[PDB]
Length: 140
Ligand SMILES: [Zn+2]
Image 1 (cartoon, rainbow, N blue to C red):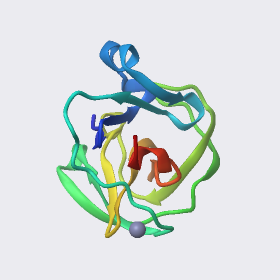
Image 2: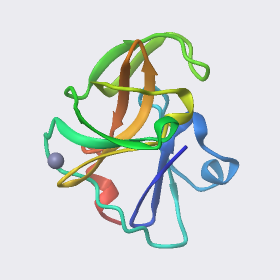
Image 3: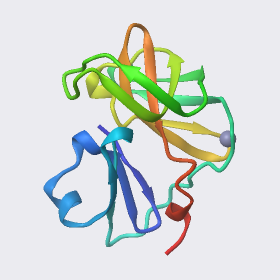
Image 4: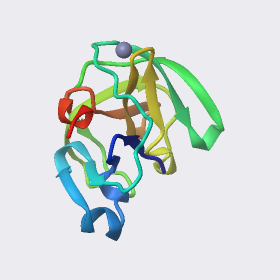
């Protein structure tokens, strides 16, 4: 589990979105596994605005923060998980690392802020849904 709280936005994995999230929907994209909802309270998270490919992500299944190198956001085939069929996922970044389904929503950060959230796993890779292209999270 996990979310990004930027301004009056909450960013979650689309597959983990709640009724409240859908009742307060701003934007969602199945192909990216992202959903953004509106919040009453101001969040304090900063979205990274950069092309960094090194960062640190939180892995809840190991209670560890792992430094990782990660790929550029791309359209990648993802094998079946407990929450999606085998399919193409867009704006996805891969690293070598541990990811169980419960690790979805772990934050990946660099010196510039939040890069993305864990969205995929298996075959010894961890996949992160990028958020750095969503410049509208910074305003409104
Ligand atoms: Zn960065």
